[PDB]
Length: 206
Ligand SMILES: [Cl-]
Ligand code: NA
Image 1: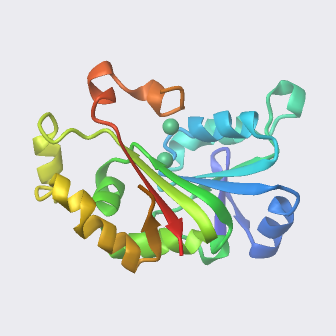
Image 2: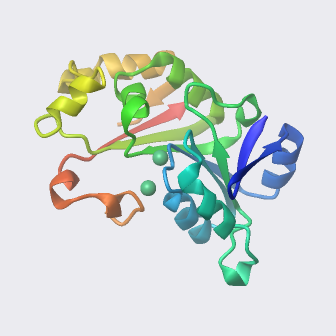
């Protein structure tokens, strides 16, 4: 089932319950590796007709955001937001085909490895979240010259510009994700130096 984060507890959500809750919304967005969930709080506030789901393997930083969104609207609550505990390697089947848009913003650790190497098992799982014709956007600011040791630690020692035009594109394509050619929540987390290293990768679910 879907592990909904409700403060410092989990509530199990069935597919039926999830479908009824998203059923009145024009679009569904999933933020994978949401971290503290700020992207979800910002997007749900900005887009009342979008249902926004933030997913992270670590629920602890989402305990308080998940309380904040439950308040009545005049106290800042967001009935179009939801936080879920899950790892990208083991996403719940109840989320299959739910999302018009999936974002992976400034991933770290295993999720950064998964989207840049990439790890095809994680790519297939991300693809399964997306409705046919929906979109995935991966945003990273890791710098090949400043972050050499972090890249090595993550198994990303072989990243080159040619990788992003060939092997990576083909791996995403084989997983059903076809490639498509800063005042955002994630842009506000970047130092000036990191801003020059931003790479945005966009794909359509096919
Ligand atoms: Cl963010
Ligand atoms: Na993200």
